[PDB]
Length: 121
Image 1 (cartoon, rainbow, N blue to C red):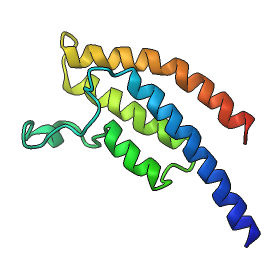
Image 2: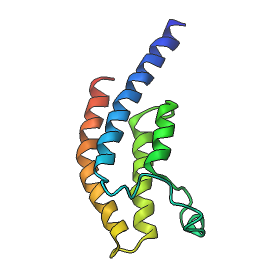
Image 3: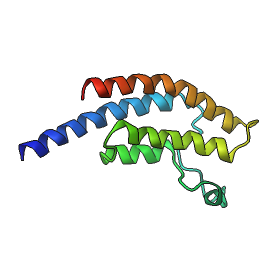
Image 4: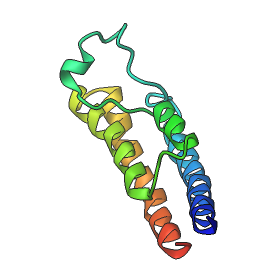
C-alpha cells in the first residue's frame, strides 16, 4: 500500500537521524571503552552480573536493520551501556569515570534529538 511505503520512508528517515545521533554519542567515547561488547572470553562471569549487555557495535547492527521504532527505544539501549558499566565497575575506575562523562555529554545530544524527532514527526 501507499501507507506502508510512507511509514517505511518515516522509519528510514528516523534511522538516518539515529545514525547521526549515534555518531555524535560515540565521539564522546574517544577511548573506545563502549565500542564493542564486553568479551566473555576476558570477563567470563560478566553475564552473572549484567543481564542485558549493550555496546555501540550492537546498537549499530540494530540501527542498520531499522530495528529502532522510535527514539525512546534507542535511548534505552544507550542508557544500558552507561548503567551496566556503573554497576559492574567501581566508582574509582577508568571505566566508571568514562561512563559518567559519556552520560553527561550525551545528555546534550539527546536533548536536541528529542526536539528533532517531535519536530519532524
